[PDB]
Length: 366
Image (cartoon, rainbow, N blue to C red):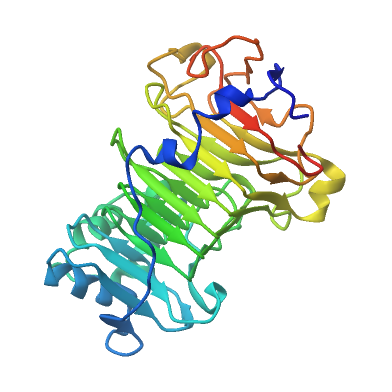
């Protein structure tokens, strides 16, 4: 139900409260440029035979002018690493549909460093601008871990990712994490894209910046567990979130924010659709979210105001009947039980409760 203030298991913003949470408000003064893939400075398939090589060319050439990297339609089994740079980059697929350009690997966090080297090592020379990223993953022991599982890794501000598909196809056990896209910087724009995985598909805001903003438009994102997770200020407008049933069909969760308690703006889902495989429709065993209580050992170790306290608003979106309609928010990764504040008067930034809220959603799951 969408009546404010809601229930302790499903709090709903008041009309007045809703006015504090809008695209403009989450943008925090950032005015995103129009995406306009109007040219190709570097073309993978007409000048570059790996994507990394085109990225490297654009970064190494320097300057302040936005550079456009076109990726010809095709399937690319490689990583794409954007190290920190002042060059604004737009990387876009050359096909008619974003499904026509696919960057994909089966590369879970559990991947050994030797296997990682075999899989991607030939993309990197020690002189290249992203070598330190590669080497930091290559130099691990045992497993590369969650950050190093990332297929497309953005550590530069002002990157635009457009009209393409990024996939980490690892579904080898029910315990594997495998990141498709990871963003670590401010002013990232993802438009008309498809982000595919299972657990930890999209690492949205992996960095420490107080202001680390990303804007997703017209984008399709799938997974089953914590498939949109992290700490950025991330806006998702006209997006689709799809809970897959092909790896698992017991107990899914979409969002896992670890938003800093002093950060007002975590995740904003607006005019979007939350849906999934039919199995969940009859199951109702998916959750909209849980807190990623990063660095918190147990529920006993949670310090209100210091520990992360994930922030998420789903507003004016379609929620299909795939979720637990009475209790869509589940236990945090720490074991900290979900607690919703449904008092008529309240502080939406209070850290003694979770910060998961809705306003004016519709559909069978609303």
